[PDB]
Amino acid sequence: MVEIAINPASEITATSAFISGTVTKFEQSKGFYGSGCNISLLYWEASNPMHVKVASSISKKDFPADISATIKDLKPHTTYQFKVTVNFYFSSSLQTFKTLALESKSTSIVSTSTPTPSMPVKVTLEHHHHHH
């Protein structure tokens, strides 16, 4: 089967969110083996699934393929749904997330540190982007 793992939506604010997934293994049919599959990770409003917006559109020919999408232009207090569309024929499972209100936090001094930030001698100056 086409195995597409979906990573839970994180870094969610009112206007943006970081979503991702991993296309572990791809299948299609004869003739389409070794094809650069267009990964379009689509998101829409839970209230309006007609507004199919593209979070990210990239091409993958190598699997497992880890893809991520940074969504901006989100509506506050709004529930959204997302899926990874791989090639012209496949879609993943459906996840849903909800944005925040117009009172969001900066999330830089205190961020959700799920991994350990233990790096012997921190050479990287994270003033451009803070790692999760």
Image (spheres, grey):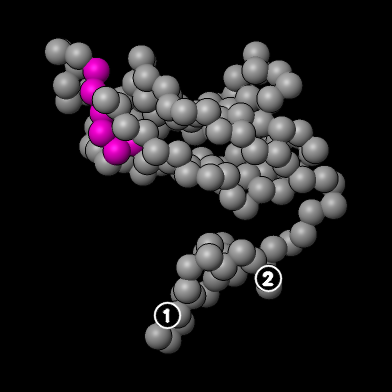
Q: Secondary structure at mark 1?
A: loop
Label 2: few (<14), some (14–19) or many (≥20) C-alpha neighbours in 10 Å:
few
Label 1: few (<14), some (14–19) or many (≥20) C-alpha neighbours in 10 Å:
few
Q: Quadrant of residue 40?
A: top left
Q: Give the left or right position of residue 55, taking residue 58 as reference.
A: right
Q: Quadrant of residue 87?
A: top left
Q: Secondary structure at mark 2?
A: loop
Q: Give the left or right position of residue 33, taking residue 129 as reference.
A: left
Q: Is residue 128 visible?
A: no
Q: Is residue 93 visible?
A: yes
Residue type of the residue flagged with mark 2: Val
Check residue 111 for magenta coloring: no
The residue under the point 76% across, 33% down is 78
Q: Position of residue 19 (x, y in %)?
A: 53, 43
* Mark before the other along the chain sequence, 1 or 2: 2
Residue type of the residue flagged with mark 1: Met
Q: Give the left or right position of residue 50, taking residue 83 as reference.
A: right
The residue under the point 40% across, 85% down is 120
Residue 119 versus residue 28 in the image, above or below: below
Q: Which residue is mark 1?
A: 119
Of residues 79 and 68, the one nearer the viewer is 79
Of residues 131 and 29, the one nearer the viewer is 29
Q: Which residue is mark 2?
A: 110
For the residues marked 1 and 2, what is the alpha-carbon distance in whole angstroms? 18 Å
Q: Position of residue 117 (x, y in %)?
A: 49, 75
Q: Quadrant of the N terminus?
A: top left
Q: Position of residue 71 (x, y in %)?
A: 60, 39
The residue under the point 69% across, 63% down is 107
The boundaries of the magenta stretch are 23-28
Residue 21 is marked as: none
